[PDB]
Image (cartoon, rainbow over all chains, first blue to last red; front, side, top):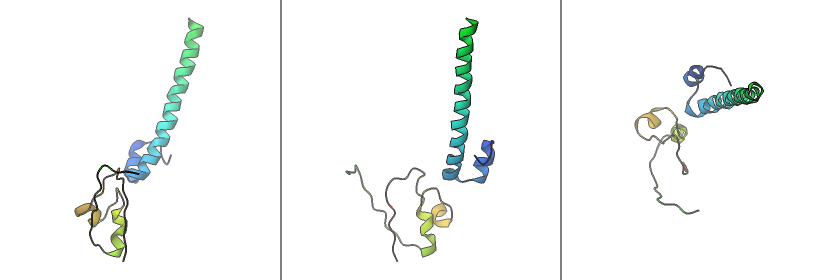
Length: 48
Length: 48
């Protein structure tokens, strides 16, 4: 995306181009969460 | 295809202003007299 800040994307672009940049941050963040929850699930099995 | 309701909106504008008939645009035709919604579905037809 053009920035890591949602307010930069939303101030500089219109609705239909900002919704293309915001979806990159949603896609990458949601994978950053899914990676954390997977390594936490795998690590919780070692602690158990 | 079949359609549940169909409306023809008919009007006349300046040939520069046809761009303002796409959804989410800006300029005084889009702003003050013929706004389309952001999730418009339909067709825009124009001729001289």
